[PDB]
Image (cartoon, rainbow over all chains, first blue to last red; front, side):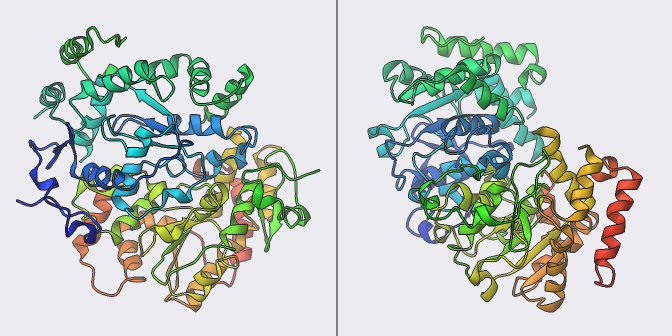
Length: 284
Length: 284
């Protein structure tokens, strides 16, 4: 009858009611999720964001990569990080490049977990500009990130793709057809999914100098194309074609299509089209 | 005729000669390795250690995991980190546990790369006690780590195992028989290998309250056994049997034996036995 007990008890001696007052669901998949600023968070993700907002101090030099919960981010982390550092750490430095020395999930911090398990971590001690990547949805960014001039890179994956993500946990740690109902309803780890996509979409169309929307499927189909387009969203000059090829070349060392059945796909397909009808965002 | 150029140019405007004065090798596998305090480092690893020593401030509360270059450390990182945090983040917290929210290579920092690519990073901002894990060999520890009371966990893998590690790079980025000659000679990324093992061995036998030596092969054979032994090297009380089982159980979601031929194995086998003859350390 009490939220779970996770870390830094101290900062929880005066902050533990807000959490215990939000709507929560249930089932067996996840324990006690809570609805915060419009979305349902696992208790873990929520305690983080909660300070992740109270403390994060953006810098116009930052660059936030936004992705969905549980889908791999390696390549998305290794990729760009390699793009920015082409002179600091030449893409030709092979074994000396940060990607051949340090795991990509230490080089590009997930605030959420940084603030979750290490609430005192000092991001101001990392080098600027900064590269990191998060799960949050628009309307929950650190005041500066919103009122600052960094650069947003939103990396979207088809829901049916993001769905399998959350599903995995339910496989590792009410069949799949049930979990889909929840996903499509929106009271599911990370949803209602059609908003953990549409505001960064309309966010990109509205203020294209701060927010960029890239589909993970196109990032894969034409990697060199999308990268040329990403580097032109937060840079200041020209980028050779061979520059982009040298980067992807370096990063080469880093689904539903086989998990859902036609009906559950169509089911999500029916909600995609609907939720995304008229918005301009069409899913392949 | 100049070492490569890697990051923070600033701190390299007065420090760049030391590097350019150490012995170096060659071949094609690696570019320009340098011998520092007895060992050969890739240029990257060396620039790190170099400040990693000038700056790191140990805390008797720390805990350093020492491992060899390139061999996977996930499970070794996920494992212990889970052991210490059994109350801060209950092993039963499943999806809320730091291991189901943050990649294990961000939770347990590799100083080397932290100091390499982020020289200003403030480790004093992480929570204590601290968990991190490094590649260095004994005689290169931060003054405090040596003159402090933290706790060393050295995780050794058979050389022929560590060898394949360094070899991999030569596969991704002079056949294998040649690389073995270098490994066995010692002027190879990380060697002379029989010392990136024997001082933490005699280090453990000499001061068993600070340095522990665990073979990765036993860590695998009897995971619950070794863990009970690790937790008793840097703790202060009793640990249930089911405690250890709950931890490994949680971490379950996280070679040469097929790469070397009998002759090259025996070749390294001939050097193991020799280098390790009389020392007490015998390899299976």
